[PDB]
Amino acid sequence: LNWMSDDRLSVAIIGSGNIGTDLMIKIMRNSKLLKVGAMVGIDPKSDGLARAQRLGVPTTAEGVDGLLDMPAFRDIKIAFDATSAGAQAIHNQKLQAHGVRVIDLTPAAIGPYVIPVVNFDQHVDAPNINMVTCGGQATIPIVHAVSKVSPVHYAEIVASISSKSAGPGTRANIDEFTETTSKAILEVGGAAQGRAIIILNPAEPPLIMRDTVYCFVSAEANIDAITDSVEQMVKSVQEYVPGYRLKQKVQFEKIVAGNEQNIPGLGWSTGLKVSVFLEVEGAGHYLPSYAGNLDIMTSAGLTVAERIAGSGVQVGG
Amino acid sequence: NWMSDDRLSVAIIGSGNIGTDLMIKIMRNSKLLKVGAMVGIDPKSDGLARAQRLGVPTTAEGVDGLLDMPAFRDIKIAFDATSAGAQAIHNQKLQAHGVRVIDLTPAAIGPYVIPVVNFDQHVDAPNINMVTCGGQATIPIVHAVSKVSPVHYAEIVASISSKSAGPGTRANIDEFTETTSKAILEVGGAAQGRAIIILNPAEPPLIMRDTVYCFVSAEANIDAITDSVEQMVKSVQEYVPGYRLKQKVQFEKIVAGNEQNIPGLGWSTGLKVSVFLEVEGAGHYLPSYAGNLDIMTSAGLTVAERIAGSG
Amino acid sequence: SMIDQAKKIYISDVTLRDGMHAIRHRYTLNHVSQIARALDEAGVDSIEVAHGDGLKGSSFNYGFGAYSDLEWISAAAEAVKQAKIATLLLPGIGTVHDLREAYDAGARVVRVATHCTEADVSRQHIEYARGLGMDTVGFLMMSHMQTPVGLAQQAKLMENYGAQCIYVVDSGGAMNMWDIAERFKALKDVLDPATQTGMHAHHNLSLGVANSLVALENGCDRVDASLTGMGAGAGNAPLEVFIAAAERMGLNHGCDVKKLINAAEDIVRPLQERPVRVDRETLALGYAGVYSSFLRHAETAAKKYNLSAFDILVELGKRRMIGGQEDMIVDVALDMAKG
Amino acid sequence: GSMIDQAKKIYISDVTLRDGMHAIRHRYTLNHVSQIARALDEAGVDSIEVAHGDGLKGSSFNYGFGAYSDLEWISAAAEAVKQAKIATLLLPGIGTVHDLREAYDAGARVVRVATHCTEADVSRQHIEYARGLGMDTVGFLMMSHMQTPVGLAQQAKLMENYGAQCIYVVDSGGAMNMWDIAERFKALKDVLDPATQTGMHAHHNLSLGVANSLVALENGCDRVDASLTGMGAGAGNAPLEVFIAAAERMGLNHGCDVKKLINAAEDIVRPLQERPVRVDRETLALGYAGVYSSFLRHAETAAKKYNLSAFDILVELGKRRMIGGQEDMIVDVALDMAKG
Ligand SMILES: O=C([O-])C(=O)[O-]
Ligand SMILES: O=C([O-])C(=O)[O-]
Ligand SMILES: [Zn+2]
Ligand SMILES: [Zn+2]
């Protein structure tokens, strides 16, 4: 364990705005397995590039073509893409051609949706990994924790995000948020039916992100086991999202004959409604406290790269 | 063989609406009365001009100027259509001369008489008070019902067109409800009495309306009440042609489970009698919508005539 | 809004007078003590107590009172420590004798209410109330039936008689905010500047709070309202709602918002029999400009004679019937049953 | 009296079968829709709004599941009307362009795309997609009391930019008085293209539903939202039959049958009311505290559940400045209060 021993996987961060820069800073502050080999941007004036060159990370304002010419590319084994879905289609083509793994923080959804605490292992070798949505990263862990104890016939999540912190891309394509998240609530969360709702609130004293998870399960679900699954899930997410916490105890509500609910997928139904009220505070070190919607994306992407790095050799073919 | 002119010479005091309408009414309808003189306070009064046109001696020097008139020596009845404070003055001057007095103010020196109810009781009364418009139209019905069964409570609503409402009523509107309740007791026969008055300026002017509420024991004969009331109506149109029922007489059983707080009694049960009158004016000088004023001149006229035929 | 947020709004409750109509004049003495106490502790300036049709409204025509005004006013006068007890007198119904009784049972405010063309019958009451030392207010009932300039001249008459405050009274709940504003303009034009003005809205078009606030904007000093609107027809301006709306405008109403909200819901609303709300029959009062106290009697007639109270009320409006003519509700019902 | 053009047609949009869903926990049957839409249609209304309380795909644990889907409700109304347009409501974040396509296929020709009154920019795709379908596209700026006249107009302009043919001042909280309404229409008229229409969606929580809709007309408004009896969230919308009866006394060109609206209100709709649609302590709270009106029955359900005042839950919800669609926060507030 010598002074000079460097066994970290060099990663490249494509995108020099908020996501890329918070991801850069989060890797340097926390990761023991990764180093930032390059930050790839598009504008020499970006504050992200300024910060990177300040921290001594190689930079280019010439897109991924600029990256491919850098001396630093030789050891880049993982690329983060925090740009655009269309750009990632092109970025991924170039990067795969050099055998570089891609973790995609855009909606391109080229590779499988991954929620790391749920289904990372299933995708350990995936050459392209999609990070779904901030809501999906926040809530699918809870859906999965419930699903483990008892089948989730219907899961529904309500993301409440401060106006200030809502991503330009989410604003431009708010439908896509609800669709991608509910899609991933099925595939990865395990629910038979999926719903995602998003609210942007402009309160002064910007709001810490809230996520509410509703799971409909059969009347004979084990209430104590669900509570323990969820509380344990929360502890797992906290390993990479420290500000992720239950705002309220796990709540349970009996839906009993004479008060059937028209639960989609089923028809009228009786059973048990599980409500999990999450608060998700961002690390607040580069992105503010109320930007939990961004902070959970970079937290989730960092931890996917870290688990990639903890598997074994990085071979760029 | 036709009539003989046995007409009584009468004096009319007051030159406005009432006195003029009583003048025209006597000259067009009486076999028994002659207007001998009219008395004003203003020589510009058109009423005084009218009387002179119709050949009636006048004075504008008040009741004082009347006693000095050469026509006064034959005056046997005088009507007062002025005010109650003036009538207190006039009564003495005419009494001292033997002149019977028919008071159309609410001064109430003499007894209240609703002619069709208690005239005969006051045939010899030297001063006779005609109560109010509402009294002259409602007490007949109260007494009609009280004939069959004793009326524990009687209440009358006088609806009068604002144009015809006389200045006396406007200036003392409490006195209207007070005079009428008093006479609802004395002359009408009710244990408790109540009178309400409403002025309405609707165009075209409303004909006078009078609603009479009677409360009697549940025993009371409904058919008999209907008969007494409808017969009394005709007894009244003998001098108020426009006086007609607007609605068939109504009756409401006040059963146990709907006790009413009749004043004077407690919470009570029994029968509620509602008769809906309408009093069109005769048209002689006052308009048809002035039934409030026409019922006064008509009732004063018929009292004067009953004196005349009594002997 | 050009309303002066600092100017104090005289808050005059009519839960125990106008509200009599909503409960067929059957408030108990304990109802009156309890409600006068809550309203007193909530900061209102006056609590009005009398039969709905005023002093001696108790009658076959309007309904018999469960207690006399004397018992009612004494109960209220005893229960309140800061508010004045107001009362209502309609010439032709109540008399100065009845006033003298009310003053001696504790009332110190009297509103003399005539129809809006008949102010000249109110002289002896306004004068006598002045002689007693009372706060003497003139009420011009059914103000929708009268032009602004016509309504103002009638206000001038009651002012000549000695009234210190004239109320625009929307007895039929028939007027909108513009009707209201035009009429306050006309009044402030001719009234002595010191003579105050008041607003007595009815909610029959759902304009009871709106009309009261607009009256304020055109110079009005006093606002009549009642808890839950408890009053004739769809009710008066709902006092807890008007106070909540005035609070949000920052107006100097000097009331406890929550106390009124709580008294309205916990004490008064449970006393309601026929719901004091805007619906087909109470809308008819406002649509056709019918005196609001007719509503329960018209529904009495509607049932007993098998007819539509709505139609009964539209026909009463068509015959231009005004306040105190409850007996014509039966007249009209009887006529419709014929044809 | 007023400066309203008594000759200008008032476009009458009924929301009985959409905002009124909130009064009936979204349990309107297909038969309620058909009967009420037919009654409304035969009384002369220009549009009848059909959707879950919270708009297309409002159905959820968050807002309450609906007895039927938007597709079946809209179809039922589309089929039962012969002159009125079937409108519907869409909240970005809840309903999507795909849900809009479905509602269009089912017979809706007006869509009102609703965002918070500071987030117009999330509505581009919906407003743009609706224009491409040839729908009357309207922009709804919810909780309009939380915005300044000028800011609200700036959001309205964005929505016009994207393709809105009409923009509504939305008093979702029922919190604004007549002057607030006027200042907002003036600000709207300063910036909007003269051809862009303008509309009022008042709630009755301070009993200003009718007054606010009239004053909007004095200030240039073209469309008035209302519903029978006020059937709607909170104390209700502008009561349609009351508004028309007041407008009729004013000689306004509304083109509706007063008595038919009055009788449908009493005879069809009010009977279906469970919790009374009226101004009382709990609905007053909505307007007093500026709280989204759909919160009312969920707040009262939490209040019964955790033994709290519904009034306090609502006031606290205002203090926290929650906005439309945030029903999950009602339980959040109730759980926090019960910890006492
Ligand atoms: O006096 C009253 O209360 C009225 O007429 O509205
Ligand atoms: O959509 C609605 O009805 C609202 O926000 O008031
Ligand atoms: Zn009143
Ligand atoms: Zn609404």
Image (cartoon, coloured by chain):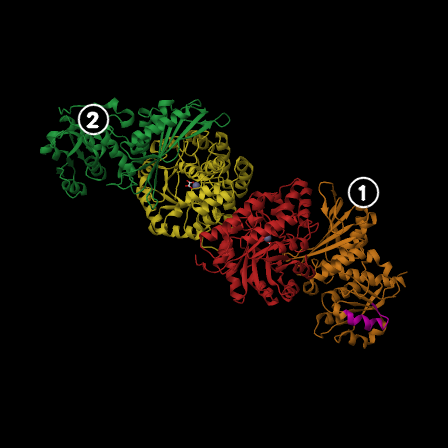
Chain colours: A green, B orange, C red, D yellow
Q: Residue at x 13, y 23 (%)?
A: A317
Q: Between residues B184 and B243, which one lies in front from this camera angle?
A: B184
Is the C-beta of the residue carrying label 2 under 8 Å from the nearest atom of ligand 2? no
Determine the main secondary structure of the stretch shown in magenta: helix
Range of magenta residues? B87-100
Q: Is residue A82 visible?
A: no
Mark 1 burial class by Cα count in 10 Å: few <14, some 14-19, many 20+:
few
Residue C55, percent from left and from top: 66, 56
- Specify the quadrant of the image occupied by residue B205: bottom right
Q: Are marks 1 and 2 on the same chain?
A: no
| Of labels 1 and 2, the one closer to you | 2
- Could you tell me which secondary element the residue under label 1 belongs to? loop
Looking at the rendered structure, the kind of residue marked 1 is Glu
Vertical arrangement, residue C39 with respect to residue A40, above or below: below
Queried whether the magenta region covers residue B97, the answer comes back as yes
Vertical arrangement, residue D340 with respect to residue B70, above or below: above
Q: Is residue D320 visible?
A: yes
Queried whether the magenta region covers residue A119, the answer comes back as no
Q: Which disc, if any, is residue B219?
A: 1
The quadrant of the picture occupied by the C terminus of chain D is top left
Mark 2 burial class by Cα count in 10 Å: few <14, some 14-19, many 20+:
many
Question: Image check: C324 left or right of A152?
Answer: right
- Can you identify the residue that label 2 sits on? A308
Residue D208, percent from left and from top: 48, 48
Check the residue under mark 1 and report the chain it is in: B
Looking at the rendered structure, the kind of residue marked 2 is Ile
Q: Between residues A200 and D4, which one lies in front from this camera angle?
A: A200
Vertical arrangement, residue D335 with respect to residue A146, above or below: below
